[PDB]
Amino acid sequence: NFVLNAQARAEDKQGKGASRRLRRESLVPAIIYGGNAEPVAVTLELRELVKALESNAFFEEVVEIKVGDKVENVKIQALQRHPAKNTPMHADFKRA
Amino acid sequence: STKNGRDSNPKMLGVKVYGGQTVTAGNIIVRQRGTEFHAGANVGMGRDHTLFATADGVVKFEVKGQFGRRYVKVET
Amino acid sequence: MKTIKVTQTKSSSHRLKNHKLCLQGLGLRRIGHTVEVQDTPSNRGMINKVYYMVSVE
Amino acid sequence: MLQPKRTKFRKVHKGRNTGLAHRGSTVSFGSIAIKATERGRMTARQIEAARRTISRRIKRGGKIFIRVFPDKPITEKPLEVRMGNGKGNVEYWVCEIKPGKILYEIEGVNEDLAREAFALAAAKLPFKTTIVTRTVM
RNA sequence: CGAAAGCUAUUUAGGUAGCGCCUCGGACGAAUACCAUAGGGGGUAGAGCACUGUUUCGGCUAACCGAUGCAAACUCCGAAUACCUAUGAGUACUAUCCGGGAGACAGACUGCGGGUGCUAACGUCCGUAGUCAAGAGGAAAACAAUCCAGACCGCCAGCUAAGGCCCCAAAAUCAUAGUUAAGUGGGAAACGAUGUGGGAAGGCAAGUCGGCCUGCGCGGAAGAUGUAACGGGG
RNA sequence: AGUAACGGAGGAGUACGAAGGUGCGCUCAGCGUGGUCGGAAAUCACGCGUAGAGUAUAAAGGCAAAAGCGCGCUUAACUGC
RNA sequence: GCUGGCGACCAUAGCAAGAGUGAACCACCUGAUCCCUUCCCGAACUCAGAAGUGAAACCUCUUAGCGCUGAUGGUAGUGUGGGAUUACCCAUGUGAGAGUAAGUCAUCGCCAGCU
Ligand SMILES: [Mg+2]
Ligand SMILES: [Mg+2]
Ligand SMILES: [Mg+2]
Ligand SMILES: [Mg+2]
Ligand SMILES: [Mg+2]
Ligand SMILES: [Mg+2]
Ligand SMILES: [Mg+2]
Ligand SMILES: [Mg+2]
Ligand SMILES: [Mg+2]
Ligand SMILES: [Mg+2]
Ligand SMILES: [Mg+2]
Ligand SMILES: [Mg+2]
Ligand SMILES: [Mg+2]
Ligand SMILES: [Mg+2]
Ligand SMILES: [Mg+2]
Ligand SMILES: [Mg+2]
């Protein structure tokens, strides 16, 4: 059982400059899709996610993402790492 | 001493009249080496594949057919 | 309606040609000059081109 | 020394080297790999030198995958000639290296020996490198 | 009032002619430009491997399949800008045409996109913007081409720009929280190292061990008249 | 659109009275099989995926109403514009 | 409800595999006498037909199997102002290609015949 404590990522926090500002303070953008609902943009914490990505069971079972009284049961779908440093930059999450 | 150093003179090919422009009958619309554009309604094609207008109207480009060709036509 | 006051702050002598024409098309003549213009989209376009040497209130 | 068997043209414009290596930057053949954290050129002589060093340390075990291939030719002018009169003659061949690109990969060795061999080979390269292992997503 | 150092041709190449760029007179006044909205066609940046080439490992019997890269003269794709047209606001003696008089056709540097050279040159050749040329004042010690700014004349008046406020020399020995001990600041790489400040984690039982990510420092560091690689004092 | 270098690569100084006009008509190349010499390739007959064939000639842009390939009749390879 | 013809559109519309139809229409089918053909051949092009069969074909229905379509988020690139000089950073505007979720076994116009 893994849990990543997220926060909402509305507009005017989406884009290229806003995402660079997010990463310059150790936060990671992410998106949640699947099911029958609309996607949900999210901000996760970098150290939390780095810690989670070291266990092989995180890639297989259902993870809980809490964006504030809203729990989502998702699986990690895709990951974007920086090419020179392996720092994760974006994560996709499929509703499961 | 080398074996290069040649070239041709320019030819000035291209689109002369764009979409939404008015034209008189006879105006050249496209100078092209092959048929990048094909002749639609009120447009003729010369011996060197020059597309020209044969009536007064307004130029319009489109894509048509089962081969997805580019056509230009004049709307009166 | 809506009207705005615009002031020229920096010099305009070594800017691009269209940036000098944007200032000339608003009524601005020198540093510290302030003019009063209508708040249309067409005026806002010129004000947006030269945001780095004008001040809007 | 690696080079293509035939090419379309002999000589090539200089060009610039910008950007990052988004494609050849994931371990895809073995367990452990050496990656470039900086940009530069890599001649065919340096490729062969690092290959020899690695395969000497590894005791002919496992496998080595070369993932860089030198296919861009470089010309020079002879000594004591003036500035005109055509382009020079092809002298050697390089691969362009953008930060992120995997250079070598090893298979079938425990990580400690692979890291010793990689530390031996990183001393013969013109840019800064790092060591990387396989990962899932 | 105010250029050009370009294009085309030349027994031409430091000459000259037509066109481009300046000026004066006449005609004619929104046709013109800037911006917004609307209608257009691209094959560049990037990317990709569908063609043309080239590259790596495997499978199968040169070729097909799987995985994996590259390209000025490859493209299944594909911008931002730029360019063309119509309509509209506001602000500008704008745009056109017809005549008199020219000069100029050796350019230079800086930034961006390139070819050539050694991604050398205060090198050379194009595109594009700024300055000089033909432009004075302030800063950069001094310093055509950098930064700020365009000098009609006069004033022992005032506010600012770039850059600055311990003394030479005008203005803070100003306030708040940190880092540096190297005169680092105030010249330089691969690489080396218990320097020192910060951060996310681990192993073992008065804590200890070594590992990563980072701010600022250390070594690597030898030249000829005189300190002489902060303008100086400091 | 245009754009320079003693920058990187290639061609031309012709051909054709049909290789021009016109009406009508056709569709390449590649592979596998069965077939007298005859074989990996002549000429047949039949199938599956196909634009990779061709164009007098270099490359590029093109080419199904084929601009590619045949047959009959012809001189519009006309005069004034 | 099954058709024939002419179009719009040009794969979310196509290829594959399966299944169905013969009143009518269409197709195969009969004969070459006449019209008309074959660089040979009634194969195809024609003509006069009507014993047959829905075998082949066409047409309509089923299944994403191959294809095609395709977000959102991020990334690359980039105009303008500033800072650095190996090609990046900051502000502001813009924004792919690839890949992921997902979608598709067609929509429509004019006419004539059948039941
Ligand atoms: Mg930006
Ligand atoms: Mg003047
Ligand atoms: Mg001259
Ligand atoms: Mg006049
Ligand atoms: Mg490119
Ligand atoms: Mg000259
Ligand atoms: Mg010049
Ligand atoms: Mg020079
Ligand atoms: Mg002079
Ligand atoms: Mg001056
Ligand atoms: Mg001065
Ligand atoms: Mg001075
Ligand atoms: Mg003082
Ligand atoms: Mg104090
Ligand atoms: Mg997007
Ligand atoms: Mg997309």
Image (spheres, coloured by chain):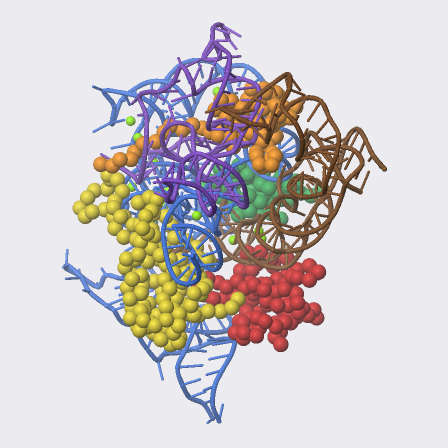
Chain colours: A red, B orange, C green, D yellow, E blue, F purple, G brown
- Tell me the quadrant of the picture where the N terminus of chain C can be found: top right
Nearest the viewer among D8 and G79 is: D8
Q: Using residue G8 as the reference point, say whether residue F60 is left or right of it.
A: left
Percent position of residue C17, x then y: 49, 37
Which residue appears at 40% of the width and 57% of the height? D98
Q: Using residue E83 as the reference point, say whether residue B5 is left or right of it.
A: left
Q: Quadrant of residue C29?
A: top right
Q: In the rendered image, is residue A23 in sight?
A: no
Percent position of residue D90, x then y: 26, 48
Percent position of residue E190, x then y: 31, 66
Percent position of residue E185, x then y: 35, 64
Nearest the viewer among C13 and F63 is: F63
Which residue appears at 37% of the width and 71% of the height? D62
Q: Quadrant of residue E115?
A: top left
Nearest the viewer among A55 and B22 is: A55
Nearest the viewer among E173 and E182 is: E182
Q: Using residue D49 as the reference point, say whether residue B25 is left or right of it.
A: right
Q: How many marks?
A: 0
